[PDB]
Every structure is written in structure tokens, then in C-alpha cells.
Image 1 (cartoon, rainbow, N blue to C red):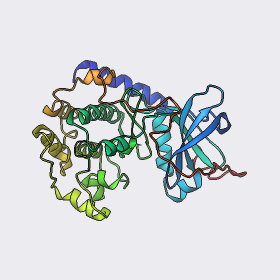
Image 2 (cartoon, rainbow, N blue to C red; image 1 turned 90 degrees about the vertical axis):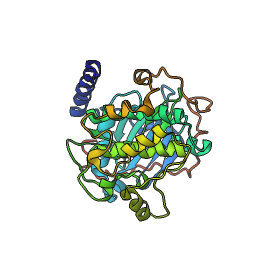
Image 3 (tube, rainbow, N blue to C red; image 1 turned 45 degrees about the vertical axis):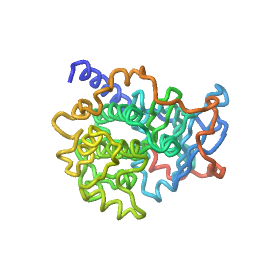
Image 4 (tube, rainbow, N blue to C red; image 1 turned 180 degrees about the vertical axis):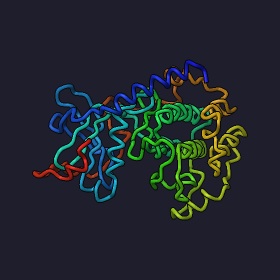
Length: 340
């Protein structure tokens, strides 16, 4: 690697480790914000558009119910998510602006990206052209180069987690499964269509699972559907482990070749996990047109800019039942979340 890249990553790791070792805590409180709209909901939390009452700035506030986190055995994951997010700094990672907790919930207040999820845009457009898919893929390659150099595995790559910003660039959101790992880790987590074979087979796995997921993402962006799908998870998993994938005839030869090397079932042969690391991907002919520095510097004109009216526009998000943000009179699960 050019010494310029080595020195960049050395400084990135220094800055990450300082924040990792002394995390920020308790940097706002709930009544500093007005609630605007629910942007998404899950089994133990929700994301809400909020507005800071003094500055007027909009944010996306992720709210996690401590009791449901415990019940659903996500304590370590939630602590991972916040400790990682408060420590990272990269152009294609969403910025955590505040965090805090109260008697009932954990809160992560992030920059609000009004353009919405890539998944919605992909399903609306149908499929992305190879140049368009390549523009997004390059950002993920650089983001994983950064995260992996910090010993971080992301473990939830999929278009739903990739927000499209006001310049048409990606912001990765949702670090709920991200983890600092030296060597191997074992947790079953992810999304079925995106799981690498070694996760399905219950092995000790490493950052190679993120490169597998990049193959899935590039395939889904360029085809409009993922490479392994079926009605039931077990049928998806059978396809993943089989070592067979079929490509649409419209895929270029270079795209097919890259994908065979990312969707390589043998992790010891998978691009991104070889002696040359990320450079086997960056130097592949499918990326021959990519100016890696210009992507990092956000100098490339994007394939499209989402349509939105301003920083508070929610048109690119869908509609959910608006439920209370209840805070108990009594502290719940204090011990489990002391470090948050």
C-alpha cells in the first residue's frame, strides 16, 4: 500500500482508540427535543425524527427499550453499537451527535439523512446500472477498509442500512451488529439473504463475512434482487452454502468475475481475505474506472440526488403508527447498561 494510505489508517486508528477507551456518555436529554415522526420500528426499538428545541436542527433518534433489549438478549450488541458509533469518523458513516439513557430507554441521536434508504430507491428504480452500483460499492469498499483496520466487523450490510444523503453519497446507519473483534467471533446475526456460509454453518468467522455481504449487495444493486432468495430462511441457507450462483445475462463479464470472488464459499479464497487484502478488490477490472481518492473526497458527481424539500422532509420514509415514548417512574436494568 502507498505510505499515504498506511499513514492515513494509522491516524484513523489512533483517533478511534482514544474515543474507544474513553467513550462519551450522557450528552443530551429527551426534553431537549420535540418528536416529529416515527421513521422505523423494530422488536426492541424505533427511530424517530426529532428537532432540537434550542438549535432547530433535525436528528434521527434511535430509541431502545432496555427491558426488550434484555429479553431479546441484545445487551452486548447495544453496548457495541453505541461505543463503536461514538468512536468512528469516516465520510460514509453516519455521525452520532448525542447519546443518553433514562429509566426505560437508551437513546442514540444521529444526523438525519432525508434522502432515505437505498432499498427504497432500488425497489423504485428496479435495478441500478453498473456505474451506479459501482459508485455505491466503492464507498462500501473504502468504509470496510476503514472499519476492518480498526478491528471492527460490520455484520449487517444491506441496502436498508445505507442512507442516501443530500449529495447522493452513502451514510451507513445501524451499527446494532457491529463488533470489535481481533480474530474470530461466533454470534449468529445478520439478515438471511446476506449471511456468509461460515455464519450459517456456526463457525468462528472474521471480517471475510463483510466482503461476502458486499458481493450480495453488488449483485442485488445490479440485478434488482439478491442472489439467494426463497420463501423460507432454510431454503435461502441451502442456496448460500451450495457454491452456486446464477448471473443475469446483462451483467458484464467483469462484474461476474468480481462476484464469483466475493461470493466465494471458501473464506480462505474470498476476495478481501487474501494476502493482498482490500487491494484485490480495488484493483479488479470492474473497478478500473473508479478514482478511489475522488470517491473518498466526495468529488465524484453522484448518480442521483434524492428528491426532498428540506432537512425536515420525511417523504422518503414510510408511515408508522405513532406510539408513546414512555419513561418509567422507576429505573429499569440499570446494572446491565451502566457503561452506556
